[PDB]
Image (spheres, rainbow, N blue to C red):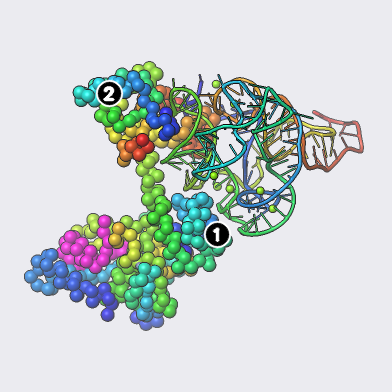
Amino acid sequence: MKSDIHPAYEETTVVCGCGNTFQTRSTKPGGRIVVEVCSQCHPFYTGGRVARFEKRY
Amino acid sequence: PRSLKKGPFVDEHLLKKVDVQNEKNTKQVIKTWSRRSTIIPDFIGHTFAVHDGRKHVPVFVTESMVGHKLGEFAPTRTFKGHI
Amino acid sequence: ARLVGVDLPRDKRMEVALTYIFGIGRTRSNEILAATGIDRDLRTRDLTEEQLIHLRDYIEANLKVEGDLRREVQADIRRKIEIGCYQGLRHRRGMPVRGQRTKTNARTRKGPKRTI
Amino acid sequence: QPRLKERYRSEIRDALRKQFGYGNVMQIPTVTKVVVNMGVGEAARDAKLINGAVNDLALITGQKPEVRRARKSIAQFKLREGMPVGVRVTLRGDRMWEFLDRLTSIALPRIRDFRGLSPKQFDGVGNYTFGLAEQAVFHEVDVDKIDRVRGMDINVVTSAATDDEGRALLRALGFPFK
RNA sequence: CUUCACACAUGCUACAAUGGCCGGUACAAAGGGCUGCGAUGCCGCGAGGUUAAGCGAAUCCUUAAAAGCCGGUCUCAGUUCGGAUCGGGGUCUGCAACUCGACCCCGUGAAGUCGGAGUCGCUAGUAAUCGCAGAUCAGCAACGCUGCGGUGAAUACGUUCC
Ligand SMILES: [Mg+2]
Ligand SMILES: [Mg+2]
Ligand SMILES: [Mg+2]
Ligand SMILES: [Mg+2]
Ligand SMILES: [Mg+2]
Ligand SMILES: [Mg+2]
Ligand SMILES: [Mg+2]
Ligand SMILES: [Mg+2]
Ligand SMILES: [Zn+2]
């Protein structure tokens, strides 16, 4: 049951446009997964009406 | 008066009624008919009896109604529903 | 080609493909593509990821798009309701707010004909 | 050797003893299993969960899922007993640490308009459950070979006794909480 | 006097490719102007602001007509069709624009894919379509009304029936 019923699963390199690169084991064919955003370059990971009248006058 | 070149519009008879109370720090109600007056940030905390057509309606200027006209809080018409 | 989490329609010219972002119409689409130098007569399938970085960061420095435009829009409607203004009461009932005629029309704010 | 595991025993295994003063190293919490399931309730009708829920959770997680049948018939759901309504995979060992690292690095920020996960979704022991809303969170499935979009909810079952002990574990692994 | 569970009536803009958008370029008529018409220059994405020439006018301003033509692009999709509704920012008029003004910018992008029974106008420079002007008027709910020119059809056997 742990033989030729499961999908193929081997080593896979992941790179980001920020410059991040690390090495996992995934199911992408060829092992060349490329992301546009990751855990290093995303926001949330690093970050009155009285003044409206004052700005007009 | 609605264009930024000429400032906002408050009636002069309404500006004199709060400047006699901003000088001695009291919060008496201002009976008024001036629905067309802008709320400015010297009306904060003041209450106003604002005429709607048939009676005067109290309105309490808090902080966020400070770019609006004063008549927007006394509704003139009345409609509960057809049935 | 996800730009700001928006999934641009594939095989579409770049002047129109940016307008599928909530917060960008045709005037902003001309001035995203003017500051970044990407030409307007370009399909979105021929886009470069090096080009996609140039306009995935021009937008947060200047513009206001999905989520934090959509919540700023629905917190302005929210603001009028608790201050008890005229438009806030008029927002609460599904009646039109900008001084519209309500005798024979306003079938956009209201639904289809109830027909009593 | 998955890199989230060698990072776990290097500093996470030792920082938890100084926050929670354990006497013995057999008390330090560790995530035991990650369970993902679909829950395709719109498969009692039309009976198509074959390409839908089975063939994408194999691509997300790495092994073929189990199909879960319904246990009692509910009339209002048009649900008959013994009918496939759920698809579930269970991840242990290296495929678990290679899922949690791949989830938090390149997948969990791909949520549209993402502002973090709630830290109050612990059940009382220190097991965390959150729900995804789309399949396009993962690059390992593609938008063009799939049927209709569907979400999934993901359990992270730990060896923790209580909630803030389990909250301190997943914070140290790299879950983003608001 | 502008309300709004609804019903009718007259119109406008639509549902697109005989079209939309962008660039270039051609050809009108009849009117208005002193509490005015504002050329030119200058600032603004724009409505506009400012300066000021000329003109009670076949003289100056209004005044760039729009369809059309040529080039480019979209490629039949609820879309680069549609432009309601709503959010924000403005300008001008006026003592004053909340109830209740018009216009401009940015965002938003609803119904609608040619319309049931029924029903209307039109026989020629007509119908269909395209702009421009006037009166009332501080401004305007002007898509109305009274006019003006542009391009420009198809049909009529016939008198039985309505
Ligand atoms: Mg009347
Ligand atoms: Mg259009
Ligand atoms: Mg043209
Ligand atoms: Mg200029
Ligand atoms: Mg052409
Ligand atoms: Mg429809
Ligand atoms: Mg069509
Ligand atoms: Mg007039
Ligand atoms: Zn990165």
Q: Amino acid at mark 1?
A: Arg
Q: Position of residue A47 (x, y in %)?
A: 30, 58
Q: Nearer the viewer, residue D178 or C62?
A: C62
Question: Is B5 situated above or below A19?
Answer: above
Say which residue label 2 marks.
B18
The residue that label 1 is drawn on is C40
Taking the magenta stretch, the answer to whether it contains residue D159 is: yes
Task: Give the camera-side residue of D134 and B59.
Answer: B59
Could you tell me which residue is drawn at 43 percent across and 33 percent down? B5
Specify the subunit that label 1 lies on.
C
Q: Which residues are magenta?
A: D153-178
Front one among C94 and E20: E20
Question: Callout 2: residue from which chain?
Answer: B
Instruction: Residue at 25% x, 21% y: name it.
Output: B20
Give the residue drawn at x 40%, y 73%: A33
How many marks do you count on the picture?
A: 2
Labels 2 & 1 near each other (Cβ < 8 A)? no
Viewed as shown, does residue E23 lie left or right of D178?
right
Q: Secondary structure at mark 1?
A: loop
